[PDB]
Image (cartoon, rainbow, N blue to C red):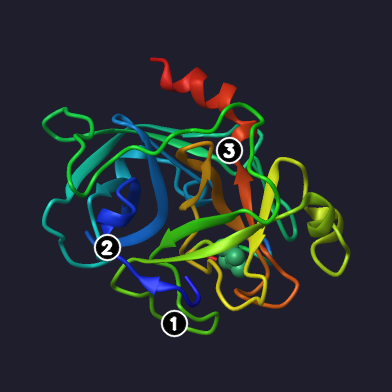
Amino acid sequence: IIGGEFTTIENQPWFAAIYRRHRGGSVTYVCGGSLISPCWVISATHCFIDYPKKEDYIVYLGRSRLNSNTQGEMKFEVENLILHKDYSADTLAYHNDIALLKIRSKEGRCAQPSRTIQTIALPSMYNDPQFGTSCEITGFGKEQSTDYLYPEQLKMTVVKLISHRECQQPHYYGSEVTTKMLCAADPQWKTDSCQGDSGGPLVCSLQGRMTLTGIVSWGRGCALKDKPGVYTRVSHFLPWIRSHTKE
Amino acid sequence: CPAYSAYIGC
Ligand SMILES: N=C(N)N1CCCCC1
């Protein structure tokens, strides 16, 4: 996250931290995600496509720090890793960048809400907030485009939804933005998601509910003028989601 | 890796 503020998991209790275990026994951070029901975390397919084996992944909930333990955190294995069959990576952009992780503890329990863990609501099918609505993004992504290290404490910031019309201007993204994506950015281009925030939530109030509107997908630099963050449009994927969350 | 990836691994 570029700019914004350090936060804790209590202020973003649906946030899931996903890590991968390597052959050496080393474990490194992969992507963010969001807890949409006790047994299900939603993220991006680009995170997993290079190594799509469920066994190699660990999901933490209730975690406020990247490489140290938070009190109240809970560790889960991945019972199913579900990538979208129509995922593709374009020269600039990703398409259908959405993934589901069914989580289970070694004990066999799904998530249990607490001070530090809660689900986030899904939007109604094809229902989004209007352009200019303020939304929240959260993650352990870089604080600067040029950084080599990731922040150890969770960060969040506010961005505003951008119209499809505006996002499609060629000085923005031109043809590469589709209606299955949402753009969002700071009106002065001062704060943004960045490398390592991918898979994480874009959360907007829609009606009276904190709602998962976007999943962090792609963008050129971070906080760079005329280049918004691009997000998977969650409202366009409910059938896909419900087909899997029924088991 | 797309040129505008945000993945740690890109
Ligand atoms: N919003 C920006 N700038 N991003 C989104 C996440 C990938 C890195 C670039």
Which three-letter amino acid code belongs to the residue tagged 2?
A: Thr
Asked whether disc 1 touches disc 3, contact meaning CB atoms under 8 Å apart, the reply is: no
Residue extending farthest to the bottom is: A146
Disc 2 target residue:
A8
Ligand 1 resides in the quarter of the picture at bottom right
Neighbor class of circle 1 (other Cα within 10 Å; few <14, some 14-19, many 20+) is: few
User: On the picture, is A121 further left or further right than A19?
Assistant: right
- Closest to the camera, between mark 1 and mark 3, is 3
- Seen at 34% across and 45% down, the residue is A14
Q: Position of residue A63 (x, y in %)?
A: 23, 56
Q: Position of residue A208 (x, y in %)?
A: 47, 37
Asked whether disc 2 touches disc 1, contact meaning CB atoms under 8 Å apart, the reply is: no
**Disc 3: residue Cβ within 8 A of ligand 1's nearest atom:** no
Q: In terms of secondary structure, where does tag 1 sit?
A: loop
- Closest to the camera, between mark 2 and mark 1, is 2
| Chain name for mark 2 | A
Disc 3 target residue:
A234
User: On the picture, is A124 further left or further right than A17?
Assistant: right
Disc 1 target residue:
A148
Whether discs 2 and 1 lie on one chain: the answer is yes
| Chain name for mark 1 | A
- Closest to the camera, between mark 3 and mark 2, is 2
Figure check: A168 above or below A81: below
Which three-letter amino acid code belongs to the residue tagged 1?
A: Tyr
Q: Position of residue A242 (x, y in %)?
A: 50, 21
Which three-letter amino acid code belongs to the residue tagged 3?
A: Val
